[PDB]
Amino acid sequence: EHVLTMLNEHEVKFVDLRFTDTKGKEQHVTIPAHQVNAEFFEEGKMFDGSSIGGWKGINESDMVLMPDASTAVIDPFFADSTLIIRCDILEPGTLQGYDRDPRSIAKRAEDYLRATGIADTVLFGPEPEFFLFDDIRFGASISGSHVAIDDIEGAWNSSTKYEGGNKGHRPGVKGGYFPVPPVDSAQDIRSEMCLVMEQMGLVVEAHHHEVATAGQNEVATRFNTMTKKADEI
Amino acid sequence: QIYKYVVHNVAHRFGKTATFMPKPMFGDNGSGMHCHMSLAKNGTNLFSGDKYAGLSEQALYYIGGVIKHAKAINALANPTTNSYKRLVPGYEAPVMLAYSARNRSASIRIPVVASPKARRIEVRFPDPAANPYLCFAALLMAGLDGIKNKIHPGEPMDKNLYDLPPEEAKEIPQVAGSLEEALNALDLDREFLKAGGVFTDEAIDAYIALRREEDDRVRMTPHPVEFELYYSV
């Protein structure tokens, strides 16, 4: 019901159904808001299993996308108002929870925790780090292969000629841990990431440039129960 | 001189350009000019004997002389600021003022050879930038002063170089660490060169003045690396 009110409150035009594959990559499919009804929540929507890597094979393609109404959150990037709803992948009819669905697996693990009675909740506080570049090029064919990385912060650009001049204040190799701007070129961006993360339900504890030259950065978020944290990741 | 001339000109004729600079590149070998020496009288090799590695006690005094006046010899055998970019705490750096028939940490190697007719010493720290004449002369005069004053060498170093060791901080004899230091040594320790009226004070002072002017260019001109290290200070 909270979902049906969020649809009106934000004048939502679409609902973006999300899930994760075995490799860990978030996937999605979109339906007009008007396709969201009572049925939707109790029986979900049907989709082809055989399309995702490592899932159903030749014979048993069809499976169920079960919206988890607790996950509803507005997408801050899409042009038209759209609501994101994370889904679990259930076996049809049985509506059990696909053996290969990583979210189902994580839920099963939280269940088993409570079952053994060892504890009733698990707490995860992961600290993912990442890189921000300007140009990334790569390829591989019979005659060779390559990868080229480029960023305005890369130490290697200390010698690069730039259109409007090289302003040269860059983090040297392993020298990214905290020089204030302009050496650190990502303050504004790290904060937008923070604000947006919070608009999406995450709670931010800190943000800072990391060690590596060429844009290594980190946004630290507050822990949460295991499955909700993986969602947060 | 002829050697250099041939090298320079054959290179030119082949479309190349040769240099005898001691360290044109950081990160790879520099160019040295090891000097093998020995003395003789009426056809006999005054350096062969029953002492260490087949040496005469005369050879040892000679070595002692070279070691005593090493820093001053440096001003002639390593007459460029660049020379000291080769003579740096490295593994194979011929900077330890000692002798040995094996330890190639020692700036004085004793070639192990069969025929006593070929017994000699190898002073390793000289570089090709050195004035033939003045470098060789300074080496001799130091050797002679080592003899005239029976300057004993001490015992041969057969342990290791500059790094580990690092036990007793390994502060044993070493060659000059900069051109200025070498020039200053030459200034103070000039007696052994003036012996026999070979080198006059005027000559020595003039030489020092020529090199100080060179040393100044390098000391006064900002170095590219200084930008890497301090532009963002």
Image (cartoon, coloured by chain):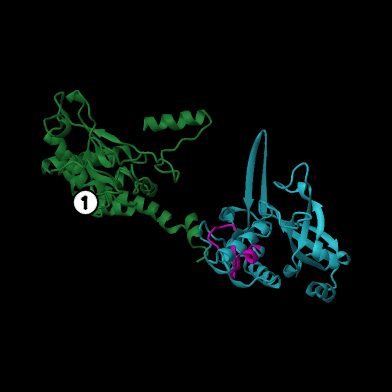
Please rate how many residues cluster around mark 1, counting C-alpha atoms within 10 Å: few if below 14, some from 14 to 19, many from 20: some
The percent coordinates of residue B215 (x first, y second) are 38, 53
**Chain letter matching colour cyan:** A
- Which quarter of the rendered picture does the N terminus of chain B lie within? top left
Tell me the residue at 65%/66% (across/down). Answer: A228
Query: Per the image, is A226 magenta?
Result: yes
**Magenta-drawn segment:** A210-230
Location of mark 1 (residue): B189
Instruction: Decide if residue A126 is in sight here.
Output: no
The percent coordinates of residue B164 (x first, y second) are 29, 49
The percent coordinates of residue B90 (x first, y second) are 35, 46
Tell me the residue at 78%/61% (across/down). Answer: A17
**Looking at the image, residue A93 lies above or below residue A138:** below
Instruction: Decide if residue A69 is in sight here.
Output: yes
| Residue A106, quarter of picture | bottom right
| Residue A117, quarter of picture | bottom right
Query: Per the image, is B230 magenta?
Result: no
Looking at the rendered structure, the secondary structure element under dot 1 is loop
**Chain letter matching colour green:** B
Host chain of mark 1: B
Q: Nearer the viewer, residue A59 or B213?
A: A59
The percent coordinates of residue A181 (x first, y second) are 58, 68
Q: Nearer the viewer, residue A21 or B93?
A: A21
Q: Which amino acid does label 1 sit on?
A: Asp
Tell me the residue at 28%/42% (across/down). Answer: B105
Exactly how many numbered labels are in the figure? Answer: 1
